[PDB]
Image (cartoon, chains in turn green, orange, red, purple):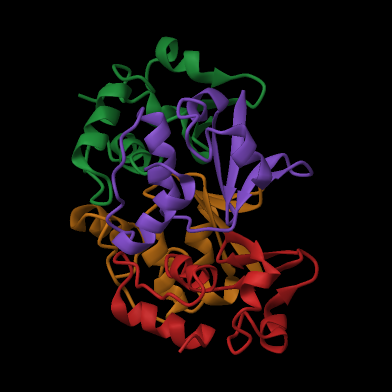
Length: 87
Length: 87
Length: 87
Length: 87
């Protein structure tokens, strides 16, 4: 019931139900997310920006609210939104 | 004597005495906090905003001081305060 | 040669030599730091503000430079400086 | 294929291929990075500023983009850039 997402060493844990809410996104779509799955460690690994992920995960947890972390530059954050397919 | 609170993968450790200071809150009230207790991992798990929790825990540690993290948006933070019942 | 400081669940690792640089401080003075030592886990535990500690540790690592983290309020940070005896 | 960089207790994980992109830097040059390698723990250890490292790692991940974290002071960050040899 609980998924582990490893973003460059920073582990995030959430419920599969939280991700499946938006099946139109990378993390909400099994076919897409599975290419990042590590069966040895049983977690999804992304070699990407760590600070931006708090806002990405919150998008799912809040049911669709997206807020840019002030500490994260606008151009860095927009690239992440595009990668995770939230737009 | 020490409690572990797991907020979306981010572990916080504090003393039970620190939480019991405010028995009128979610974390200070055994009946409320226990529904989030995971006996397998022996920790309380919250699938919620990670950045906001530093200020939530500090509220207990400082004996009642609540300060909003600049890096956390006002509307996101207020929802957390309501959830943890600090108001 | 390496010490582990656990601040409310957030682990920091540094070298004993880095702390001993300022023997006039809490962390640089064996008699003071030892009352926070946990022999079971072999780490020093502080049930205190997590965000402020990055600047506290950097004080030792930089050889005396103290900068307040913008994300940490001035009154919260000053209380930490007083506790760790850096002034 | 995956490297672990331990910055004062904060673990970062990336791919060796991500670092080797810039062989002219500390982390991209085997001869330089190896003096910080810990064979016992199998990770590279740096007793340095933690907040600055997110932007340092992102430099490699983004293929050369360097942005200063607002929460990190300009003079602290510049010292890190010099140490990791990104300039």
